[PDB]
Image (cartoon, rainbow, N blue to C red):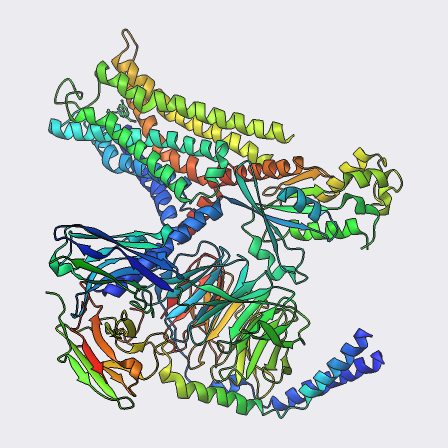
Amino acid sequence: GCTLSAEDKAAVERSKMIDRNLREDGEKAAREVKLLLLGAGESGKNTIVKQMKITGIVETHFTFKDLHFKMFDVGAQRSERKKWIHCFEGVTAIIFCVALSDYDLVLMNRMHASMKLFDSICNNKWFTDTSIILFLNKKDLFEEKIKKSPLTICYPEYAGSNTYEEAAAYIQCQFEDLNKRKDTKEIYTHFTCSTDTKNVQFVFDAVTDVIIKNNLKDCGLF
Amino acid sequence: YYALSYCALILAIVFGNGLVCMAVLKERALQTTTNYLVVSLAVADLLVATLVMPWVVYLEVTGGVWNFSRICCDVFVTLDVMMCTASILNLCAISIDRYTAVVMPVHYQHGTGQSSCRRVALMITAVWVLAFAVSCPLLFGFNTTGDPTVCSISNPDFVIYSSVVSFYLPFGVTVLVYARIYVVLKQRRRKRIPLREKKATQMVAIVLGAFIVCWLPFFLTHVLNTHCQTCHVSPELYSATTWLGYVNSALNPVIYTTFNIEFRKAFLKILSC
Amino acid sequence: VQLVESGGGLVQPGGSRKLSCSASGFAFSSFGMHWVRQAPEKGLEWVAYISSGSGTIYYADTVKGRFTISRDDPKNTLFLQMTSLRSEDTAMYYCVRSIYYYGSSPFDFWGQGTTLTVSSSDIVMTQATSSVPVTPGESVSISCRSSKSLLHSNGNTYLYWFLQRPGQSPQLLIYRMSNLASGVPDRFSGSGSGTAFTLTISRLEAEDVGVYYCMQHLEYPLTFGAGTKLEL
Amino acid sequence: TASIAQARKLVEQLKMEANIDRIKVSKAAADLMAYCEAHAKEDPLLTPVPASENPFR
Amino acid sequence: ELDQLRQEAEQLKNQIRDARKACADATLSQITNNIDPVGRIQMRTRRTLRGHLAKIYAMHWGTDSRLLVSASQDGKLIIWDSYTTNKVHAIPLRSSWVMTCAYAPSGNYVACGGLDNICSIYNLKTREGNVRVSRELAGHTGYLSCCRFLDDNQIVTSSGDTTCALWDIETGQQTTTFTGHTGDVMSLSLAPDTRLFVSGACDASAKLWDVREGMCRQTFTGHESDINAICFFPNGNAFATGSDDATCRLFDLRADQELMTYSHDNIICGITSVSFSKSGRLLLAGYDDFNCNVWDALKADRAGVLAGHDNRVSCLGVTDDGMAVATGSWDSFLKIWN
Ligand SMILES: CCCN(CCc1cccs1)[C@H]1CCc2c(O)cccc2C1
């Protein structure tokens, strides 16, 4: 077009070369799984981050079976969550950490604090569609403690055994019953320990189910 | 009977597939790769209702009598095989898109990325090119209609090839593809061990159900008018089943858009304005 | 920031040489690049342009088809393959940076040049002068004129002023008629009507000795004035 | 203790705010009104400029 | 000790609101009822500014009224020529989690930051021709919620740690900290002279600060909910705030109180962003419900609507010459209006 100078034409060419790089970086960013990592302070987040990798946001990258995952640990932030949690509205899944051993530990009870955090995150207006991966992080130390101290420290409402199976299953249900919005959200719970591969495989499995369900929304099947 | 019912169908198809085109034109939440196929379906159904079906009205009004040049018969007949094969092959392309959503889920994962848009630009091109490739022989020596006072397709050397490539092939592929989608979704649930995974089974059933119910009785009756010896086949059954074939274009907005929330939101906005 | 340039010396007419220009200490891929010729004791002539990412190429008609401008961004290197050389090509060739965005300074850096000794409707820019003998401390007012108005519909006036000191490559003084370049002292200022232009050296210094070229950037081919020398 | 240090700091701050030479709201309201009337002609959003001199044609 | 200090604090709170109430002889409405209305403000989108691929969180105009920076959660800080729609620069951020950006009064620098707790300063005008990180202002302990340059070497930044800080950029050092907010500070506005700034916070409070003396001069408290947005009126004697209350409020410095509020009964959503027109007569506010409302700042009549966005209007800026308003959005577009 004759209306543009030789320098306007070269500025439009630069602008279009910037578009080409913005679009390419958007293609790179779209093939990356955004994971928000949540849970209380000692909840096993650091054990998860070690296994996945093997103040302000700690953003950590891992690759597993050609999915690229970005993990946002928002734990070192100390500030009003409703002012910044909406940055994460486009997250694939939340990973929520619970120290399973903290049913009988003090913050007033740590498992009830983890459940109040889980409820506020799960039932949040920014995450209505967003699935959650629960890691129940310390099944070994929970087996050591449950033999010694009952779940009635956390849940006087409970009526099962202090065997691992009934206690661990009851805690999973005490988190998964915090789902409102069961029409649009799923929780992917996984009992967790010192374990290198299975937890990363569980993120990949649960994220693949989440991506499939997002695709099935995008073509009307879900 | 049929003449004014086709006029109601032209309005129903222009309204329904016009809403699909308008909703994707307005709503950027609908401007996915995934819905550009559903607009390609809507364009095929619009060109059926606007180009093809008024000639179906007037041909049925005259009682099957053609009052125009054989150049014009080739145009009507090629547009019919074109726009109907484009509707049918869009159903098949949408099934292969929905299969990519499930079996190649990482590639699909946002319905707007350049490699996904490239994939539907390719399969929309394949839909419209293959619709041309099966219809274009009727611009020349394959439209052997027996007398210039009539305009219809009736020769075995074309009707088999045409019914196969336009329907029995993409029908078999679409049934195979949606059955494989239903199987892979059942395998996802089995491997994990819900109401919207049951919705996917309901949508597979509604999609194959409408595609069978509209198009299969036409392509059976079409092959049986031409290639069968001693059949009890009739112009009544052929007129009934061609009407039931064009009814697919009236159902296609229902099937591919009214069961999706982003489409219902966009339609309720357009219906409000 | 550097542009270091090689290929040069003697070559026969009808012959060919690859000039190369290795960039360092700047984001080479983001700059458009020019070649500018200077024939011995003559003025500057723009030769070729390649944009950032090679999407645009231009040439002067004196070299179009006969020279090819090429670029290797991963090697930070610019090339001029000269395919059929003639005596009119004997010159120092300068590799020159340019970058184009709102408020940018194109032509801002010029390499040390490389000398090629070939063995033996454009906008006209005129300076109506060739030399000016003058003394430090006093003001000087160099001038230039264009055959076409350099004031574009967007409100820019596309003059550039260059100073070339003795034995040195050109330096941008003023870009887009009014604006002085980075590392140029406020002693230099530019002004003009859209067809006539002035470079004022408000207090002359011994470093201001050299040939001053106007150049237009309204349209390709880019065209320089003949050059006006200041001397003590 | 830190809470007593903050209670002293908060008293000192509330005292430093209390001792301010506040003007009447009628005068202050009239001064914003006067700034708007003075600059009304100078505001392209309040009074759209003709398309000849609007940069955003 | 503590009960007497709490009684003295409450007694000073009685004395200060008594002093505000003694200033309140007439309201701005009673003084502006006799003035002519603005009429309908019917701005058109003159530009749409497309290349961001996530939510726009912030934008800032250059003082030239032509360049604007904008920041998105896709980890890009884009400088736009608003006249041509050209991207002048796209700057890759080290943290994608950007919540604010600023453009220096010179145009030499942009600043941005967010959930990284750092304000990164980008030199635009390098001899290398790329944009470089020149400094990282680490020292806040919560997210960077706002940045505003005073000049090429001084920037005031606001944080989720409930503090503002003034920085010397060349030392990389917070030379002043401003601490009196009890909630997360969300927004800044420098006064036109840059001697003062206001900051609005999650304790529903706005504080006036002296930049040089490092002290809260005044506190303003009429909001029922957290202040997301703050802007000086162009004279520097008043400022508007927008909050999750779904109201804007205009506050005097000189009379130390709220003049007026800007809300309609059908507005029920947080105000994300606030700006004045050049005369101060229009107060522009950006909202969730996805639009910008223009207010007659003198009457509190809703003078017009900028209805062009499909997701939350996250940003406003009126240009310094007043020619246009840019509005930025979570729908990933910037729209420019006249
Ligand atoms: C519902 C579609 C009816 N048409 C019927 C042709 C008509 C005759 C009289 C009135 S209309 C078919 C003709 C045969 C064919 C085909 O072999 C392949 C792909 C499409 C079609 C379109």
Where in the figure is residue E211, as x and y percent of width and height?
58, 82
* On screen, residue C118 above or below D43: above
Left or right of B122, for residue C126: left
Residue C60: x %, y % from top left: 16, 60
Regarding residue E287, the answer to whether it shows in the image is yes
Q: Left or right? Give the position of B46 relative to B24.
A: left
Q: Where is residue B246 in the image (x, y as percent from the top left)?
A: 32, 30
Residue drawn at point x = 61 percent, y = 68 percent = E159
Nearest to the observer: residue E240 or residue A208:
A208
User: How many numbered marks appear?
Assistant: 0
> Whole-percent x and y of residue B106?
49, 38
Tell me the quarter of the image containing the N terminus of chain A: bottom left
Which one is in front, A156 or A151? A151
Q: In which quarter of the image is residue B236?
A: top left
Task: Check the image and name the residue furthest to the right.
Answer: A148
**Residue B109 placement, left or right of D44:** right
Q: Which of C60 and B230 is in front in this view?
A: C60
> Residue at 19% across / 56% down in the picture?
C10
Q: Name above or below for residue B155 compared with residue A47.
A: above
Where residue C231 sits, quadrant-wise, is bottom left
Q: Is residue E276 above or below residue A191?
A: below
- Viewer-proximal residue among E68 and A120: E68
On the rendering, which quadrant does ligand 1 occupy?
top left
Taking the image as shown, residue C88 lies to the left or right of residue C213, namely left
